[PDB]
Amino acid sequence: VPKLPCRVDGACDATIIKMMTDLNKKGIKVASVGQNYLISIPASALFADQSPRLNWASYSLLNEIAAFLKQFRKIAITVTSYSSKYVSVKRERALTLARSRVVSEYLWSQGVDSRIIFTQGLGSDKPITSYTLGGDRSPNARVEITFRRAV
Amino acid sequence: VPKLPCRVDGACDATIIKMMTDLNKKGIKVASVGQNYLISIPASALFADQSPRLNWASYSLLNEIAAFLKQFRKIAITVTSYSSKYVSVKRERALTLARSRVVSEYLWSQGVDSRIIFTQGLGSDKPITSYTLGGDRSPNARVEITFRRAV
Amino acid sequence: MKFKKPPINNPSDDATIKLAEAAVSVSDSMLEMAKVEKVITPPSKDNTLTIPNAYNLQARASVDWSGPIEELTARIAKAAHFRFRVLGKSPSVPVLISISTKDESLAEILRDIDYQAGKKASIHVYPNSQVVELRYAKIY
Amino acid sequence: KFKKPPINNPSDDATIKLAEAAVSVSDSMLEMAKVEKVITPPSKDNTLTIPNAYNLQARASVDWSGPIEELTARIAKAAHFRFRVLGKSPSVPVLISISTKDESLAEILRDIDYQAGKKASIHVYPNSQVVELRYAK
Amino acid sequence: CFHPPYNNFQPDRRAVKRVGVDTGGGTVGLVASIYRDSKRKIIRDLQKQDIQYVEYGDTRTLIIPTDKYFMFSSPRLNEICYPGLNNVIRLLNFYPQSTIYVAGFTDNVGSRSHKRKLSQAQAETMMTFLWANGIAAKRLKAEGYGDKNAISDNAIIHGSAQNRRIEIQWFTS
Amino acid sequence: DGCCSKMGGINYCDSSAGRLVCNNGFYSTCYCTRHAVMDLQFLMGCCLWHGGVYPQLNSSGLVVCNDGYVSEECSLQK
Amino acid sequence: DGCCSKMGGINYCDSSAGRLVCNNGFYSTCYCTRHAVMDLQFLMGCCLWHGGVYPQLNSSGLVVCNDGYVSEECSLQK
Amino acid sequence: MYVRTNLTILSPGWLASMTSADGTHAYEMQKSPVLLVSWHGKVMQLKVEGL
Amino acid sequence: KETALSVGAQAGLAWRAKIIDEQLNKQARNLDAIYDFNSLVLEHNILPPVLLEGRNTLNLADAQSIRISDRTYKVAKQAHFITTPPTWRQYLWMDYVKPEAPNVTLLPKTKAEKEIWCIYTERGWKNGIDQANTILEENIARIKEDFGGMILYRKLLAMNMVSPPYVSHTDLGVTGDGSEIHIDDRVLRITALPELNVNSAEWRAAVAK
């Protein structure tokens, strides 16, 4: 006990439940089924209008994401990007790929002790609704991040 | 402390900084980049007009600049002279060489422990001011001592 | 009118000083090592013939792994939705590789895995059938 | 608002040299391996390709470590193919060892030929349903 | 009112906010703007940051440290030190005539080709960042030297850190 | 006493050059490790430029270096 | 200290996982078994990466590892 | 010393190794108080008493 | 007395050691990046040997006897088999033990005793600091020596001035009695140790471009 750690470092699951509740209060989707965890973020809350540029206000949200993400001992994080339909196919594919690349690059710069970060973006191939009113206003244009908690 | 010398003999950083600021207030150009130091002295406040003769007041300036130059451990010094375009090529060239010889001789008689004193002068080949209205008053004619502090 | 020089940073440490002092010497030795090897034997062919790249391999990855080989390969196969296959048998001595890199194509990741594998193993892709195959060496 | 700097940044003037040395030694050793590896072209690789007949698409869990002939006759009878031999069996048996849970008999045969090496080879004729084991002298 | 990412490349307006919050005296706000935008205070703030400014003869030069005004082992630019870049563009607006030379410098670790490649990349990145802020393309020249000439030495670590640098020169006519 | 006095101040003792680093980027006038470059010209000690002092306990006031040559100033006066 | 705090509380210790179970269906961040997946990046002791300390002792404070190495940094000097 | 686990021992060397049908590993080594393994690429140590 | 000085030397040695191990652990990844061994291992899991090269040597044997050599080469440790790549943790990781015994005899009672206590303690402390750094630099020198010898073997084999190792393997089928059996037998032996060559024709000269 004086030489062995009583817990994993930086762990306060009370604070984890608090920040998870606060995340859903913000409206960023937190999904927990089994040991697989899903976080979903609307793209309008992250980028400009079909642009691969980070809004400068969003870095606080990103810091909150990393503070949550540092908690759980993990292996692999998958990042998927989804968009609307704007001009062509490969244009949307490229924009999604760039967006997922940027968030993966900043997160891998940050301290999340994964071993694997996979990233891909697919454009508008798997929508989550038939409601297609806006462009980036529509909720299907989004970024999802998934992982499996291990042990 | 009783046998180990704490600092290098006969040098203090406060003295170095104060005398460097005094030189800059006097208007003699002093520049420090990396481990390299360049000191530039205008000709008009030192020599006679286009002629290798010395005012009696100039020995005071040579005195204090030698006292500053003793503060650093040195290895090799370079003395280079620059003049104005006056009559010829070789007349100005030999004037530069004579001026360099005099200042190098007095410095070598003074207490700088350089292993190497190099001396040369180039006349009026490379200027540093295209405004060449003045004669010896114009700042393109001067002398420079350049050296590198080692370890 | 005070003076400054452009590097000004956090404090250092003597152990790091001596470590870098060793490291630059090993770097120089490895550099001339590689140069004299490169001249003394001619390169023939890079692995790009036996592993090309195709569609859906272009998803990207940041990877730090320092263990055995085939489970990392299986993770990559699960990423690519490509069917895994082993050929030969693993030796009793495990084959260990270390990867510290970031933001590459999976095709070049697997090429680097093949290059770090040495003579112990090889890897091929059959993209028409979407099969990722790892073959062992048939010695011992 | 707050763009955070990287956390494990090389903020020491010695450790930036250390990291640069790490980059240099990584690229140089990668070059060393690249110039020293020997590869084979897939234009004439000596691996048995897939026969893609319908008789050879089933799944099995098979474990064996021993002689070759009983195992290959059994998988031939499983695939309803006749089995034939060419050459003389050596004094020592050519030993193979395959243990797997769920894949197909085509790649079973492929892995058998890959572990065969220079001692023997295998052949499949699907028009006349035959499987031939060819020894080497 | 302002954006920390380079104010979206706009021609900025700083002193109007200053005189507005000073009215919240017009003359004292205006002379406070004068004292803030005065060139000596610009240079003193540049020296408060880690930026070296040399003026000599008619040619003026600037020295930038790579490790705080770059990202490591990359042509990526650190976003934290944007006040230095804003001050750089603010100062270089004063000399709208002569041409500009930029040079990149490394230490002596690794392949010579690698050093030359990295220096070329850094020089091109700094050049095009200068290009985007308003000065047109015919007045710019970029060059990345390796370790071919140094202001310092490389046997001692802090000297080696002083060696790697970015150099800016501009003439007058 | 202040090695980086009336300036930025002490950063650290670099052991490569054996010098303090001032916060303004200059090497100090002081020293911090014994493996530095000092202008050493004057020494102490006895039986120098020979085998050193032979460290035995002698019965008399004679003291002899390890080469066999003696030193009467190292020895006493009687 | 409260491992499954701010939930229903501690259910029990799953020793296959070596982990506590919270009363809601979520894993704790504490442990209960010494056979647990814990990261270990700092150690104590002497003669590490060697044969270990010798059970026999020296008359002096010299300590000798089992593989013949002698560790002055554990030993006492003079 | 004799050890049975399912991890991959790295540092102090060994003399005899065995693997079961299910990846269970058994090793025979010299006595040492510290072991080194790679769990999932992350490297870890093991503290062993009784020596 | 001097007991405070000695125990302060012990404490300073311990504290410098703990901070050194902390820093050495925290800088982790580039360390094993630059000290690879498994990329350097040979074909049959053989640790390749270590070689030493000396240039332009002069010996005076005695009064009026001298020998001059241009380059000398020496095999330090003979190559052998191995089951694991050696790592830096058996070269660099210092030992650590908390010293829990300040002998409570000579506690101060007067301020002069406190003064001499303080000064003797700090000079012992700096002694312990310098001793620990000496241990660290000896360790880094020895591991640098090991790696240098290994890579020098690699480039001598590139320059065709050493024999490669030679290995024969014998193969048997099933063996043993009716109660103990083994499916296969592979006996892996090495006959020829790697060694230098002495002739003149086989020297392979290098060039660059």
Image (cartoon, coloured by chain):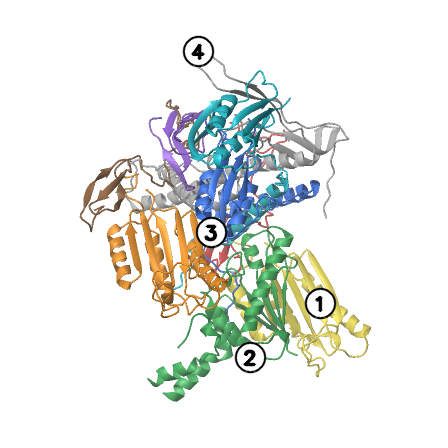
Chain colours: A orange, B yellow, C blue, D cyan, E green, F red, G brown, H purple
Asked which quadrant contains residue B94, the reply is bottom right
Q: Residues under labels 4 and 1: Cα distance? A: 98 Å
Question: How far separated are the C-alphas under marks 2 and 4?
Answer: 98 Å
Which chain is indicated by disc 4? I
What chain letter is assigned to the residue under label 2?
E
Q: What's under tag 4, amino acid-wise?
A: Gly
Mark nearest the camera among 2 and 4 is: 4
Q: Percent from the top left, x then y, of residue F52? A: 58, 34
Q: Label 3 marks which chain's residue?
A: C
Q: Residue furthest front?
A: D128
Give the spatial CA distance, label 2 vs label 3. Answer: 46 Å
Query: Which labelled disc corresponds to residue B80?
Result: 1
Real-space Cα distance between discs 4 and 3? Answer: 54 Å
* Residue B102, above or below A35: below
Position in image of residue D116 (x %, y %): 56, 27
- Tell me the element at label 3: strand
| Residue bearing the label numbered 4 | I178
- Quadrant of the rendered structure where residue I166 is? top right
List x then y, in percent, for residue A146. Answer: 36, 52
The residue under label 3 is C61
